[PDB]
């Protein structure tokens, strides 16, 4: 039971890991891997207008670069773990 | 093992011994008892009774068909089904592979190497067919010394 | 030119039948402008049945 | 010097602490792989030397071995008895989320060091007794990997004793061995 | 030569239908037994006039009904006819390897095998080659005639010995 | 610019070959003249849309014929004693015995009995009446019409997508795993839960009562509150009759395992949970690659970073992302390799674990459905290997793939071909020698002298699954294993009851004949892999001919010189391995149909005594089951298997007709057609008629293709007939 506390703590734990623990691990990997590259150029550089990386949606005011996509990524793992926990407890 | 009864206590294996002699006994009914073709069927029956008493005494496993099944996993009871005659085979098959390999090395350093393969040099052949007796000590000996394998720089390779 | 007459060479030409094979040089042409002057004889024939082929000195090394 | 007379390889010169030249399969032959293997051999060993007192001293005080004190999480109710006392916060989603937060913050801060020597032995806050800033420095690092490899072999022993004899612990394997030592050995596992 | 090679197949087709018509025609209308009061019971009584006009009768009342003595001859004196019936099917399907394939595929497969021999220093000086195109067709038609003719030999010599 | 207009070099051909090759080079879009990247990808995209429209216009007519001329409601009332009707027959060539004999299933006229398992499928999924199938047929007519509109739309210059959109592999994988594999299996789960489970429990849920018929007693409350076990609370009992409310439960997502005890089929609550699991895991796996939002993966740097530092893989996978993304034949070969391994995983898991209600009882339908996916999978896997060969000729760049794993396959290609050759030769001598030995011992009156090998490895795997027949008792058959105690409260009460039953096909009792034919199967896969790996790796060149890449993929030969170069091309290795897949899948489906045709009538001892030697295969399977096949029509009369008796003979025509193209070769027929051209040009009253195409013989590649296609059509029709006439005429 206790859906309102289990989901909130598990999302807040994965967002704590996403902001303070694994954020140098994630920011290094999105720069080392970079954008996807076909034949030496970016997909947007090759002519795909739909492959342009959005910057208004990625314009974050967090001082460590933690954006709303990382909210939608690390918080999605916190609900996947949070519903893993709730299904395991309620058995 | 694997749901198979032993053939010495298998009722289906004893049924096949009963219906094989009975087939041969009915073949014997139309011959004279001292005739020459009746001695062949009488030798066939004693060959059959020797066979069924040999299969049951070796710890063979018989299924629901009354037939002896071989366990080739490497069981300590079942070594003579696959492991013991497999090591007997591979020794003989490696003997064939070692004296044919050593013959080709002995005729490659000859004046006409292609006339020694259509016309096999029997004094050269028989002096190494004896030498194929001790071939695991000579194959791994050539493997450890590097003489068994050829380096890829001296091997004819088709282009990419 | 050439490595030597009567010497053992190994063919580096990819499309030859005798690639990475021991061959014996029988003739090197010293005339200028010849692309493949070194004539190498092999103990084994190819599928055409010949053993005589001409290679450049860049496609052979001494072995 | 893991074998007297054996030629030590060119990538193992002996200047490293515990460089006894033991690499028959050549796993550390790559230079950049070998720098990761040196900081992997020490974290493993330090976790193993935190594990041998974590196995024997719970067993010698009578609170079970390291297996029967670990099966409570698979049970829906185990209550997490620590030193004979059930902790109130000892639930499986509670203690795993702390372990996936506290250790992950510790291991991410460990991996952030760019120096390949401070990754091995950091010092400073992790050396408050000042033995690193002392007269002996080389032999204590040799003491680290000789004690560490002993506990690494010990934890390998610890694990495969539980697979071979389930329901028993390493001091209970020691007490079984101390009664009739010429009958109950690894040959009971080798020869069934 | 290739026309002789194809005429060998058409000789198989011609002569095989000739001996099939022979075997069915006289097992149905000639060969049999005579009981009392002049009644003639043939081996396959009167079915040549009605079943040998369709290919299903030829497959059914000749190739299936009369092959009920070449396949259950096992455990008897005619079991070598069953063994050579099956091995004749083997030689026929072995012929289809040589007939349908060509030389260059087998030459490059032999080149891979020669590479494996060069690796272990067991290269023969007589170079392994694929069979020639005339030779591959000859080997294929030899196994086709041998396997099919041995199939008909085994089926005939089991059936008409069994019912004779 | 005549036909064909895509190739200028074939339009100037004055012969019949221009008519032929334009049919066969019609979809080889990259070999066309004046041909570019954008036109390649857009024509392939619209051809995909046309393929989707053909599939949906096929399903629409297979639904329309069941709804119109089939007794789907009468099969829904009694699925055990009613034959499923495919479609009606209107043949002007029937006599009155043929009309009176093809009238089956209580129909008003001559009808065809459906052996495609569409009735079992549509019953399990929720379709009950003919009006529901008609509405599905109209809906899929609309869906195929929408795909035709979308295919026409993307060839218009306003909506043409560029090659950079086509080569966007990360966005394609994210929206395929998230959308195609995730939201469609979650859509499915919404069907299976909303419609198929209440139609199994008698409740009629349609579009009119979708928003009112609650799928659970407490729906979407326990889902969002976390207690998901409420959805596994009250499962269907063992007294549940399918389609009726009595004996039913309320749980929508169970984890029971095993089979429904009345249908011998999988539980719709389990398949609903199965799809919610392969839906959560595919939507989560679809958030992997980087498209537009900063997070994700670039697969180029994944393949670049996956290099072993010891140099055993060379450069690893560096340069492989551009190699796959630039080569359409690499992507198509990977897709067909995965598709063959899953069309065969389809075949292996719908006979042993029947997923559709009353499919296990209908025997010939199950036989057709196994043989279907094993032949479609042995042509899809060979297409994968053939496309690997076409990649190595017209798409593999050795400069871009420098010392990576793909270049290192060419570096040691003789080792791979020679070791596949050794494995094929090992399996062939051993399997043939053991079958011929067992044949000799049954011939020589001694069945006991056979080398019979109990397949104890796969029997150990069956005992590892829970089969207590062999008595190995290691794990899931012994109660002392942790896997059993982790499973005995969760799924194993269904699974052990399903696997310890001896009437079903779930992990059958195997014997020495199964061992021997599994080595026949390994022989077939190994030799087909031998020819196909040999074609793919000697595609660019070999020691006989080093410039095979500059002659294209499907070139005939290289001439009689250098010994002879017949079948030297990689297409010819594909050609020679179509015979090997036909032989392989023939062995596979022979083993399936005889292991099951003896299981279904009870006497498994016939297979256990007779499958170890090939005279048992010839006599007790090929001869014994063909008793009512070839007696489908007689001089006395004709039965309902008569169409299957003609289709059997028809196969023996077409297959043997292929021999005419596979044995006799071109120049005989070219001189024959030269004499025919003289005869037409000199015959009075017929010389007036001219040809515009010059009559020539079939060309060499075309001859091998025509003989191969005839061989394949005869092979699939001889076995489709025998297999659907030796199980449907002797049911059991
Ligand atoms: C002189 C002895 C000799 C040696 C040591 C080997 C050893 C080798 N051969 Mg073999 N082979 C030989 C004779 C030899 N062969 C001859 C005479 C033929 C023509 C029949 C071939 C045809 C051949 C094929 C078709 C294949 C091999 C391959 C192999 C390898 C595995 C063994 C195998 O497949 O079973 C042996 C295979 C046979 C077909 C049996 C032939 C062996 C004969 C009976 C020995 C005769 C020797 C005697 C002195 C004359 C190994 C490298 C495989 C490979 O590519 O390497 C992995 C493979 O595909 N060989
Ligand atoms: C998604 C599956 C798929 C796709 C679209 C491709 C795509 C293509 N294949 Mg492929 N292929 C595959 C699977 C598929 N194939 C399978 C299933 C097989 C095994 C039977 C092959 C075997 C095959 C060969 C080996 C050849 C192609 C070639 C081609 C081209 C079409 C040639 C054409 O117009 O044929 C038209 C064909 C006919 C009119 C004959 C059909 C008659 C039937 C069988 C009766 C095109 C690149 C050719 C190519 O790329 O040329 C270099 C080529 O040579 N394919
Ligand atoms: C969520 C978004 C979305 C979704 C739904 C799809 C959907 C699809 N795209 Mg697409 N794509 C997208 C966005 C999307 N894409 C993006 C953003 C990119 C840009 C890079 C592309 C670019 C792209 C290309 C360029 C191509 C596709 C194609 C396709 C089709 C795949 C072929 C097909 O129908 O097989 C259907 C396959 C499945 C349903 C998956 C089934 C998986 C296995 C094989 C079967 C398992 C199912 C189960 C066991 C069977 C039971 C059923 C049985 C009872 C009958 C499919 C309609 C191709 C096509 O056909 O074009 C028309 C094509 O050419 N798309
Ligand atoms: C893409 C998949 C899909 C879609 C379109 C729907 C659509 C619907 N579901 Mg549903 N369902 C699905 C997945 C799907 N289902 C799966 C994954 C489950 C299994 C857990 C169920 C089980 C479920 C329950 C048990 C109920 C619905 C209900 C609903 C309805 C309203 C949902 C709402 O209020 O929010 C709607 C018809 C609710 C309803 O009122 O239906 C009548 C309801 O309570 N769903
Ligand atoms: C009793 C009957 C018997 C007979 C007739 C055969 C027949 C054959 N076997 Mg087989 N086999 C048998 C017993 C039998 N096997 C047993 C009991 C074993 C178990 C160990 C095997 C395992 C086996 C192996 C491992 C190999 C043979 C090979 C051979 C073939 C070539 C051997 C040769 O000339 O050496 C050629 C020279 C060699 C060096 C190869 C020998 C393998 C070395 C020793 C390893 C030959 C056709 C080969 C085969 O079929 O694969 C192509 C082969 O590789 N067999
Ligand atoms: C009964 C018929 C039959 C037989 C036995 C052969 C024989 C064989 N096939 Mg196949 N094949 C056949 C028909 C058959 N095939 C037909 C119809 C075609 C279609 C055109 C092909 C085309 C062909 C190709 C394309 C390939 C094979 C290969 C081979 C070998 C497979 C390895 C093996 O099993 O060694 C065991 C040997 C036997 C079972 C023959 C036993 C004969 C005994 C020793 C006589 C005493 C072997 C020589 C492959 C090969 O040679 O590589 C190794 C190869 O790549 N086959
Ligand atoms: C290269 C040859 C080869 C290949 C392709 C196969 C292929 C097959 N065998 Mg195996 N097996 C082989 C030789 C081989 N076997 C030999 C030499 C033996 C001793 C006679 C066995 C004994 C064996 C048994 C007892 C069973 C199989 C089974 C199987 C399957 C699973 C794989 C397995 O257990 O292999 C294991 C492979 C080995 C032990 C040897 C590998 C090859 C060496 C080097 C020769 C597969 C269909 C199962 C089966 O038929 O399913 C019903 C089964 O249970 N195999
Ligand atoms: C006993 C210890 C044995 C260690 C020997 C291993 C050793 O010698 O390393 C050799 C090789 C490592 O090569 P890499 O180039 O990856 O690594 C360079 C090494 O020097 C490590 O630094 O490993 C293997 O080939 C993998 C063998 C295990 C294969 C695992 C297969 C997994 C299957 C899928 C699951
Ligand atoms: C501290 C701080 C702050 C705040 C922040 C916050 C408050 C945050 C929150 C956050 C959040 C609030 C987040 C959330 C997120 C969420 C999400 C993102 C979700 C998702 C989900 C998912 C996706 C799931 C899934 C699923 C499903 C649907 C079903 C099936 C199962 C699963 C579970 C898988 C600020 C800025 C002021 C600044 C200062 C500091
Ligand atoms: C030439 C070429 C190609 C092709 C190739 C091919 C076609 C191949 C195939 C291959 C294949 C087709 C393969 C498959 C594979 C699979 C596998 C390998 C599987 C495995 C599995 C596993 C390992 C799993 C596991 C397990 C088990 C076993 C039991 C229990 C459960 C589990 C899950 C745990 C391409 C196109 C690329 C291009 C280039 C060239
Ligand atoms: C298989 C095959 C080959 C290869 C056939 C070969 C290499 C013949 C093999 C003959 C024997 C088996 C090898 C020589 C045997 C030696 C006498 C050594 C004895 C070893 C054992 C037999 C004892 C072709 O060359 C060919 C050419 C044209 C169309 C089709 C085909 C074709 O199908
Ligand atoms: S034309 Fe025919 S016979 Fe002549 S080389 Fe080509 S494939 Fe061989």
Image (cartoon, coloured by chain):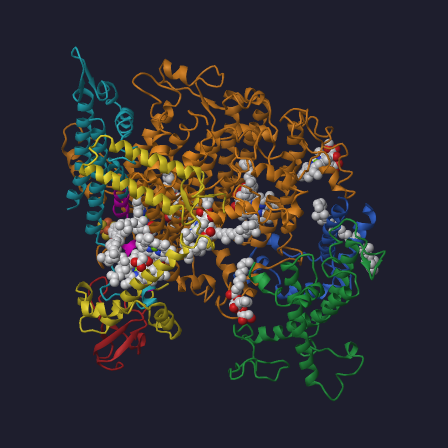
Chain colours: A blue, B yellow, C red, D green, E cyan, F orange
Label tally: 0
Whole-percent x, y for residue B92 in the image:
32, 61
Q: Residue furthest bottom?
A: D135
Which residue is located at x 61 percent, y 52 percent?
A: A50
Q: Main secondary structure of the magenta part?
A: helix
Asked whether E7 or F569 is in front, the reply is E7
Q: Within the magenta stretch, is there residue E102? A: yes
- Is F583 situated left or right of D64 in this image? left
Asked whether F39 or F583 is in front, the reply is F583
Asked whether E109 or F518 is in front, the reply is F518
Q: Residue furthest front?
A: B34
Q: Within the magenta stretch, is there residue B60? A: no
Ligand 11 shows up in the quarter that is bottom left
| Residue F469 seen by the camera | yes
Whole-percent x, y for residue D17 in the image:
64, 81
| Residue E111 seen by the camera | no
* Rendered image quadrant of residue A61: bottom right
- Give the residues drawn in magenta, as a range: E91-115
Whole-percent x, y for residue B98 in the image:
30, 66
Q: Up-down: is E55 above or below F282? A: above
Q: Up-down: is E22 above or below F326? A: above
- Is E123 situated left or right of F457 in this image? left
- Is D40 situated left or right of B17 in this image? right
Q: Quadrant of the N terminus of chain F?
A: top left
Whole-percent x, y for residue F66 in the image:
52, 24
Which residue is located at x 75 percent, y 83 percent?
A: D132
* Rendered image quadrant of residue F725: top left
């Amino acid at each position: 039971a206790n859906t309102a506390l289990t989901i909130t703590l598990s999302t807040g734990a994965l967002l704590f890991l996403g902001r303070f623990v694994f954020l140098p691990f994630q920011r290094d990997n999105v720069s080392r891997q970079g954008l996807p590259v076909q034949n030496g150029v970016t997909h947007f550089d090759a002519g795909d207008s739909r492959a342009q990386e959005v910057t208004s949606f990625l314009k974050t005011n967090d001082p460590a670069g933690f954006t709303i996509v990382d909210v939608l990524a690390w918080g999605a793992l916190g609900h996947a773990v949070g519903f893993f926990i709730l299904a395991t407890i309620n058995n | 093992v694997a749901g198979l009864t032993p053939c010495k206590e298998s009722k289906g294996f004893a049924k096949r011994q009963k219906q094989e002699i009975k087939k041969l006994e009915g073949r014997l009914k139309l011959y004279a008892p001292d005739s020459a073709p009746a001695l062949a069927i009488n030798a066939t029956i004693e060959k059959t009774k020797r066979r069924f008493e040999f299969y049951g005494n070796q710890g063979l496993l018989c299924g629901t068909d009354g037939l002896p099944h071989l366990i080739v996993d490497g069981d300590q009871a079942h070594l003579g089904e696959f492991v013991y005659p497999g090591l007997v085979f591979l020794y003989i098959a490696g003997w064939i592979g070692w004296v044919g390999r050593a013959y080709l090395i002995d005729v490659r350093t000859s004046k006409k190497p292609t006339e020694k393969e259509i016309i096999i040099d029997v004094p050269l052949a028989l002096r190494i067919m004896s030498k194929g007796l001790t071939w695991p000590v000579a194959a791994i000996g050539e493997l450890r010394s590097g003489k068994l394998v050829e380096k890829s720089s001296n091997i004819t390779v088709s282009p990419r | 030119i050439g490595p030597k007459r009567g010497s053992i060479v190994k063919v580096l030409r990819r499309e030859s039948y005798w690639f990475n094979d021991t061959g014996k040089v029988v003739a090197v042409d010293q005339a200028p402008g010849v692309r493949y002057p070194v004539v190498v004889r092999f103990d084994k024939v190819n599928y055409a049945g010949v053993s005589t082929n001409n290679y450049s000195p860049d496609e052979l090394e001494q072995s | 010097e893991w074998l007297p007379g054996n030629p030590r390889p060119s990538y193992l010169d002996g200047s490293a602490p515990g460089d006894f030249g033991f690499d028959p399969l050549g796993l550390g032959e790559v230079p950049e792989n070998l720098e990761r293997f040196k900081e992997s051999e020490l974290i493993h060993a330090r976790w193993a030397m935190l594990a041998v007192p974590g196995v024997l001293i719970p067993e010698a005080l009578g609170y079970g071995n390291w297996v029967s004190a670990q099966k409570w999480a698979a049970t829906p109710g185990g209550q997490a008895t620590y030193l004979g006392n059930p902790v109130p916060w000892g639930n499986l989603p509670v203690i795993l989320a702390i372990e996936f937060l506290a250790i992950a913050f510790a291991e991410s801060q460990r991996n952030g060091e760019p120096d390949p020597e401070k990754r091995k032995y950091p010092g400073g806050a992790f050396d408050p007794l000042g033995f690193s800033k002392g007269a002996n420095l080389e032999e204590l690092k040799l003491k680290e990997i000789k004690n560490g490899r002993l506990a690494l072999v010990a934890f390998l022993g610890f694990a495969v004793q539980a697979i071979a004899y389930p329901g028993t612990g390493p001091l209970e394997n020691l007490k079984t061995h101390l009664a009739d030592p010429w009958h109950n050995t690894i040959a009971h596992v080798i020869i069934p | 030569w290739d026309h002789v090679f194809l005429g060998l197949f058409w000789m198989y087709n011609a002569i095989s239908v000739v001996i099939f018509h022979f075997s069915w025609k006289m097992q149905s209308d000639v060969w049999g037994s005579i009981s009392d009061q002049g009644v003639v019971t043939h081996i396959t009584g009167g079915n040549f006039a009605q079943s040998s006009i369709t290919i299903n009768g030829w497959l059914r009342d000749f190739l299936w009904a009369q092959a009920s003595q070449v396949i259950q001859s096992y455990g008897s004196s005619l079991s070598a006819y069953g063994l050579l019936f099956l091995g004749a099917h083997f030689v026929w399907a072995f012929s289809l390897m040589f007939l349908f394939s060509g030389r260059g595929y087998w030459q490059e497969l032999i080149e891979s095998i020669v590479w494996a021999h060069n690796k272990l220093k067991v290269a023969p000086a007589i170079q392994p080659r694929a069979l020639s195109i005339v030779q591959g067709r000859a080997v294929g038609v030899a196994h086709y005639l041998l396997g099919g003719i041995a199939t008909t030999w085994a089926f005939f010599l089991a059936r008409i010995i069994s019912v004779g | 610019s005549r036909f064909p207009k895509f190739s200028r070099g074939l339009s100037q051909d004055p012969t019949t070959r221009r008519i032929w090759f334009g049919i066969a080079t019609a979809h080889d879009f990259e070999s066309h003249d004046d041909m570019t990247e954008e036109r390649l990808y857009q024509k392939i995209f619209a051809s995909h849309f046309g393929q989707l429209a053909i599939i949906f216009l096929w399903t629409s007519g297979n639904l329309f014929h069941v709804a119109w001329q089939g007794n789907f409601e009468a099969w829904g009332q009694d699925p055990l004693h009613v034959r499923p009707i495919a479609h009606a027959i209107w043949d002007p060539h029937f006599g009155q015995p043929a009309v009176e004999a093809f009238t089956r299933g209580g129909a008003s006229g001559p009808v065809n009995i459906a052996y495609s398992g569409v009735y079992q499928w549509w019953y399990t999924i929720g379709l009950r009446t003919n009006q529901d199938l008609y509405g599905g047929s109209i809906f899929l007519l609309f869906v195929s019409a929408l795909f035709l509109i979308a295919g026409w739309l993307h060839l218009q210059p306003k909506w043409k997508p560029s090659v950079s959109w086509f080569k966007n592999a990360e966005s394609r994988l994210n929206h395929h795993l998230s959308g195609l594999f995730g939201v469609s299996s979650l859509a499915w789960t919404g069907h299976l839960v909303h419609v198929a489970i209440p139609e199994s429990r008698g409740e009629h849920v349609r579009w009119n009562n979708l928003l009112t018929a609650l799928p659970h007693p407490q729906g979407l409350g326990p889902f969002f509150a976390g207690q998901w076990n409420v959805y596994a609370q009250n499962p269907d009992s063992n007294s549940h009759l399918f389609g009726t409310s009595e004996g039913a439960g309320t749980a929508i997502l169970t984890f029971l395992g095993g089979f429904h005890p009345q249908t011998q089929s999988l539980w719709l609550t389990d398949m609903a949970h199965h799809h919610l699991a392969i839906a959560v895991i595919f939507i989560i796996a679809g958030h992997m690659y980087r498209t537009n939002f900063g997070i994700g993966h670039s697969m180029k740097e994944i393949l670049e970073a996956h290099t072993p530092p010891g140099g055993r893989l060379g450069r690893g996978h560096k340069g492989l992302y551009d190699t796959i993304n630039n080569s359409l034949h690499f992507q198509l070969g990977l897709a067909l390799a995965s598709l063959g391994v899953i069309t065969s995983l389809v075949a292996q898991h719908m006979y042993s674990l029947p997923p559709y209600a009353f499919l296990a009882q209908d025997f010939t339908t199950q036989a057709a459905l196994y043989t279907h996916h094993q032949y479609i999978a042995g042509f899809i896997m060979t297409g994968a290997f053939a496309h690997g060969a076409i990649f190595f000729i017209r798409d593999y760049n050795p400069e871009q793939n420098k010392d990576n794993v793909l270049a290192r396959m060419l570096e040691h290609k003789e080792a791979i071909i020679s070791h596949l050759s050794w494995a094929s030769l090992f399996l062939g001598f051993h399997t043939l020698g053991l079958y011929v030995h067992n044949d000799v011992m049954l011939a020589f009156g001694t069945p006991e002298k056979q080398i019979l090998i109990e397949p104890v490895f796969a029997q150990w795997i069956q005992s590892a699954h829970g089969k207590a027949l062999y008595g190995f008792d290691v794990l899931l058959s012994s109660a002392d294993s942790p896997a059993f105690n982790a499973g005995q409260t969760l799924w194993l009460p269904g699974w052990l009851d399903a696997i310890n039953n001896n009437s079903n096909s779930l992990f059958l009792t195997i014997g020495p004949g199964d061992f021997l034919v599994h080595h026949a199967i390994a022989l077939g896969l190994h030799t087909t892999t031998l020819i196909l790996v040999k074609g793919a790796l000697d595609a660019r060149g070999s020691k006989l001919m080093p410039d095979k890449k500059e002659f294209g993929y499907s070139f005939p030969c290289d001439g009689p010189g250098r010994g002879g170069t017949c079948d030297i091309s990689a297409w010819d290795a594909f050609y020679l391995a179509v015979f090997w897949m036909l032989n392989t899948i023939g062995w596979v489906t022979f083993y399936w149909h005889w292991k099951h045709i003896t299981l279904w009538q009870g006497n498994v001892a016939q297979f256990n005594e007779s499958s170890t030697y090939l005279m048992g295969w010839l006599r007790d399977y090929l001869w014994l089951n063909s008793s009512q096949l070839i007696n489908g029509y007689n001089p006395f009369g004709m039965n309902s298997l008569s169409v299957w008796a003609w289709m059997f003979l028809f196969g023996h025509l077409v297959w043997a007709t292929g021999f005419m193209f596979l044995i006799s070769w071109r120049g005989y027929w070219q001189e024959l057609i030269e004499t025919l051209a003289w005869a037409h040009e000199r015959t009075p009253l017929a010389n007036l008629v001219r040809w515009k195409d010059k009559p020539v013989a079939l060309s060499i590649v075309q001859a091998r293709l025509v003989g191969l296609a005839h061989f394949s059509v005869g092979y699939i029709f001889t076995y489709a007939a025998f297999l659907i006439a030796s199980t449907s005429g002797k049911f059991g």
